[PDB]
Length: 422
Ligand SMILES: C[C@H](O)COCC(COC[C@@H](C)O)(COC[C@@H](C)O)COC[C@@H](C)O
Ligand SMILES: [Zn+2]
Ligand SMILES: [Zn+2]
Ligand SMILES: [Zn+2]
Image 1 (spheres, protein in one colour):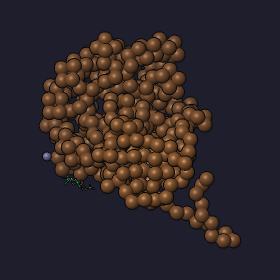
Image 2 (image 1 turned 90 degrees about the vertical axis):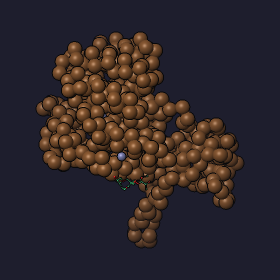
Image 3 (image 1 turned 135 degrees about the vertical axis):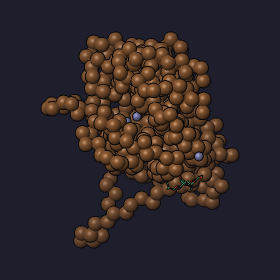
Image 4 (image 1 turned 60 degrees about the vertical axis):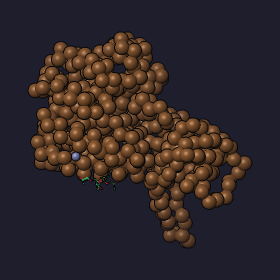
């Protein structure tokens, strides 16, 4: 029974802090006068950084761990990736989905992630993965709050019975309504699909998260419809546009006009840097575009944007350990957010901003909130990011659910010396 966390650093704060726990909540946060000694019922942060848990705002748990089955994505494009998935989706079973989803979820728990939004392909008359994932959500609840997006991978209007399947997924309990307007057969189907998505979200009172303009096409502007509909319904906080990689290729005048609406609408954005850098720019020769959405500009404008991993060893991405600091590292480089302050504040892109994207209410290190928090063996966000630190402890409801004993490196020169890379 933990009653206290001691010797903790907090972002943007001086010295050490003591975090008092009570009934699985944070009761108080008090400054320390110095390093406190270990005591029974206390957890020693060892002068590490305490932050709320990492969030994964965008992952595909139904496809995770399937790379190469039955074939590899040779071109490394979104479009072949969908072809490869269709082959694998025909082989999906209930147990298959749950086994693979849980494998990745365990990596996530180990990585201090306590909030996850997974998209699940509902372009499937049997709804096999969706129904399986609704079970996983209940099973993993003690460790991760999992949101499920009903994601119509092959289109709402462009797939047989797509709209009916999407609605059935909501009836069954999916938390979020998805869409994919740039993959619909026509621009008109794309726009109409968004009207249907918003209608369903209002009917069932659910969140929205659209796979939006994931394509190097300067004419793909479905994001403006997502934002306009959100604004009209007054529901911006409940709405997310994922990817928006087309925005990387927009002219600046249109982008300027668009940003006014994006800010007024209050919708959220997810960028997926590991996957975006891999899949975008594939139809360029040289020079080759980066293909990530306008993260730096969004931040400058106070538009909420955050980072997701998207894919973990699957048709779209052959790598990954579900690590959010690694995602952040890629995002900072590709988006050129490389100022000291920008790097130090980078933690926000995988914590607070992502919590806002998931519409979370019980999140943050504050008295009254659930005792959900993680401890990094690092002095601040910059240090954590530079050294790619593991999660020392993950605490949920005041209980430790994960811990990492950090690696220990020694060099043998004239005498043994410990190396910490600081
Ligand atoms: C994926 C690999 O690491 C093994 O996990 C087994 C697991 C067992 O199900 C537990 C559930 C509460 O009934 C998940 O383990 C989490 C427990 C220990 O809390 C899921 O296995 C899925 C198969 C059996 O279709
Ligand atoms: Zn079942
Ligand atoms: Zn993806
Ligand atoms: Zn996705």
